């Protein structure tokens, strides 16, 4: 990544073993559960495009997912090129293309130069945006259950049903009452409109 | 977070893999046991609103809880807006709204600017306050037992009963004597008023 | 805690995940075995009162113990107030009360100001003293066995008996010979007065 | 490796226990699965040739592979010598040969001198290139299955088949439709040309 | 401990969780096997007397041993007082007694002052010497087997016998040939005088 | 070890718990497998002779090996004394003997002085050389199998046989074809002279 040193200047730092292992392990343990994406963003704090490719490329499984991610990246790269066309002068900074932002046709030194320029061109942040767009698509696709099929069981605790409900909703990206069981539904209808989730959970506890 | 460098200046630092893993693991292991909240506050020392959202968003389970937390946050944000209304000048610092403090409509750079200003606007501390208010509500709700049902068993050691008692009281947020068993109750009544917990525990040991 | 930076100045540092986890785990593994207290003191090196409360508050179990600790703290705080009464001037440092030293009614900024003043008011050290006083009381109370009941078994190795003996003595806070078994007692009496523990252990080996 | 200190200057740093252990463990766990190579490159960020040899030499197993890697290295070293022949002056920097880049006939001090010169001679980067060329050959050789034999099972989920497909393709370094099972093949043919992988996976889900 | 900062000055640093845990765990795993002592010395690199007491005091088991260690320390402290008697001036450095070196009657600040003085009084090093003297006595005492009873079994590999031999010798602090079995003894006698251990091991392999 | 600080100056740093544990664990897990030696060299990067003795002395097992290592060290020390004889002036640096390089008769301060002098006397590097010479002798001795007895099994995969072959060769410090099984031998003879290992492995796959 690029970080501020002890004296304030922006400089490159190697991606740590800790960071590398943390990402690989969370993918192994959580697959494409929605919470993996906030973890990805935090672990890639200050990342260059090289760092972002490292993280994605260190993943061993899920190659269907990783190929879909490349497609999304290539769509975002193409749209960047459509909005930001480029036409170099000796010792001067060239303008980044889509593939340069994706770390494919740019060197680490060039990425550092764009990221630390004044004004800066935040190629790590632009690429992470594209990557997260792609990851969100995968999270949605690999969501195993529709929200329409999350219904409260006859003796399922309401808290457990609401957990299942908002877990599914998060992945998929009124109905809570409708999908409740008969006993809690009668209690929830009695509360009337504008009841908070807290109030609903308290009532069916 | 925002920390002081080796030369004393306030600068941003990436949230660590250690911090990220520590929070996720304590939620997995302890759920909403009351001691999780002091752990949350300590792990979020110097945190930006972005950092606070990272920590909450990396939690995979308990989505009923996390949705309740959003409601509480939105109530606190709204009250902030009622007390601190806002009406920008080129290159000048805008005033934060509720949603800016919650990290929803503010950038990392803006959060850094408020937090490091002179005088500072401590948006990380204000948001953590709101989050802990919400977490305390959840801890209370998910408390499994009323203090009225913590009673000493016939041959339960007094120490074990007092542990259960103050564990429950902590979550729920004279009676100790009343809920004691007959043998220890007779001993505790004999001590008279103003006895310390130490004195009570010594007597029923 | 408060530490010296690379250039020598006293500044605040966030309590680490390593420190937080180390304390919680030693309490879980050792409860109130006497060696926990030296571990507590070392893990709280340079700690503010806020840091000390964090450590105590992150403990999930043993709430009977933690309530007794609060009583002890409140007794020490009251005695501080009796010896150090307080009667503020704009932008000037106020005098700490008992509750300020215990971190209850003082901010982190105030604690930093007292701790880094010239001359300093070491509120972290004063509070740790009170906490350790309270912990020692608990260690003594939760000591399972009187030293009078640590007696050497008929075929118990002397080394194993002496370990049990000084383990118990440590928790409770001539007799070694008296509580020895007949065979070793005869050997130990033959050594005469002024024999070292080493000499005693060698003789009964 | 060679890193920038707090004040910006390029200096040598010892390879860490963390880095050493991370590499050895990933080889033990993943052998020559293709994702090991991006891990190797990241763990060797800023590495000297000495560091690169350390990493390779700490591997205990797979000596057939490591001997093949030496052959590849020696081929690249020889080609370097063919393009960059060398003909020293007291206290002056000599030109590196193939074996100097491979860390065989060069000292650490010489490697540091080439790497930190102005203009620099990036001997760590040149050698890592050679090593990765050799590793890619091994990954291909140790690929257990041809892409021609990755066919969808009668009731294998399409996602699981695509994972197997792109896993194999990655190691080996239209057909996806042809190797699909009859049911999904009929669905995929109906989509027509130019369908994305996402569209294909959605259709056969 | 006391370490050099980034700018070269000698300053106090808190004992780390890593150091604290490493010592406690090696005692738990190895007891008083002789290799524990080099580990103790290395883990206490730069230690103050306070740090040394922390390490010893964090040990939960082996209180017979720890009481013997106190006796040894008190003997060394007394001898220090006999050689270095002491007779203070406002704001001036007092001379250390035995108990000050052992960290019993000295503050951390005083220990820092002696250790960082010019010329320095290395109270951490003097105390570690006393502690290691005491630990060596315990290692010898807790050695389970005399070297006279380490004899090669009829079909015990010579390497395994020599390991047992020098393991025992290390703890206890010509005979190798005499204690060998008949077959290897005949081979070893044939080598004649002045044979190396390597030569002996090669011959009986 | 001795490292460069943030400002470039050569200063002593304590050996880390991480380094100490890493060495002890690799010896426990790998014994004297040949890959332990590159691990030793890397873990002892920048080591003083004191550090090197620490690492060797923290090893609990294998005392036959460690005694052989002392013999080798003493032979190298004696040869140093034969080539570098020594004949001190107040406040001046004395010349190191063999035993000073081995850390036996030299202080840490003296080792630091030699290592950081201009010109430096690299006593850590000279001693590590001697130690590795000794370790290589042990690796060879403890090699369980001659290369002459590594022969391919009737249905052993060629890759598995080549792994065994170069594993043994590494420890021991044309034949590959001769020791192959009849089926692969016929294939390998057909390739003719000058075939690479890659080509051989491909052919017998």
Image: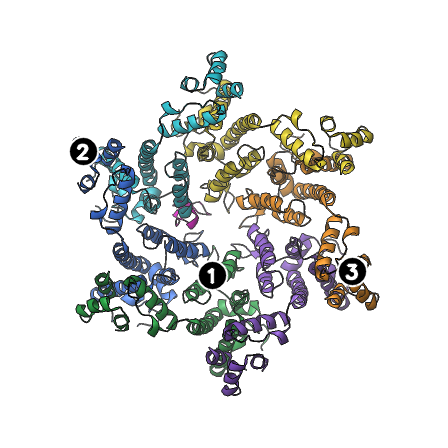
Chain colours: A blue, B cyan, C yellow, D green, E orange, F purple
Q: Where does the image place residue F65, in percent across and percent down from the top left? A: 69, 60
Q: Is residue E131 left or right of residue B119?
A: right
Task: State the residue in front, F25 or C41.
Answer: F25
Q: Quarter of the image containing the C terminus of chain D?
A: bottom left
Q: Residues within 10 Å of mark 2 (few under 14, many from 20)?
A: few
Q: Which residue is mark 2?
A: A186
Q: Which residue is mark 3?
A: E181
Check the image and report above or below for C87 versus D155.
above
Q: Secondary structure at mark 1?
A: helix
Q: Secondary structure at mark 2?
A: helix
Q: Which residue is mark 1?
A: D29
Spatial CA distance of label 3 from label 2 is: 89 Å
Q: Is residue D128 left or right of residue E43?
A: left
Spatial CA distance of label 1 from label 3 is: 44 Å
- Identify the subunit bearing mark 1: D
Q: Range of the magenta residues?
A: B1-18
B16 drawn magenta? yes
């Amino acid at each position: 990544p690029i970080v501020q040193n002890l004296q304030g200047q922006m400089v490159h730092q190697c991606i740590s073993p800790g960071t590398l292992n943390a990402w690989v392990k969370v993918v192994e343990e959580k697959a494409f559960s929605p919470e993996v994406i906030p973890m990805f963003s935090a672990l890639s704090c200050g990342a260059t495009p090289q760092d972002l490719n490292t993280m994605l490329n260190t993943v061993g499984g899920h190659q269907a997912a990783m190929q879909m991610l490349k497609e999304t990246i290539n769509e975002e790269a193409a749209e960047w090129d459509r909005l930001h066309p480029v036409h170099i002068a000796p010792g001067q900074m060239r303008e980044p293309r889509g593939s340069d932002i994706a770390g494919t046709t740019s060197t680490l030194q060039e990425q550092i130069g764009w990221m630390t320029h004044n004004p800066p061109i935040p190629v790590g942040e632009i690429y992470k945006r594209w990557i997260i767009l792609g990851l969100n698509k995968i999270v949605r696709m690999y969501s195993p259950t529709s929200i329409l099929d999350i219904r409260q069981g006859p003796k399922e605790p309401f808290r457990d049903y609401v957990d299942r409900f908002y877990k599914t909703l998060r992945a998929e990206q009124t109905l809570l009452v409708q999908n409740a069981n008969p006993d809690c539904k009668t209690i929830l209808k009695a509360l009337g409109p504008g009841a908070t989730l807290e109030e609903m959970m308290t009532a069916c506890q």
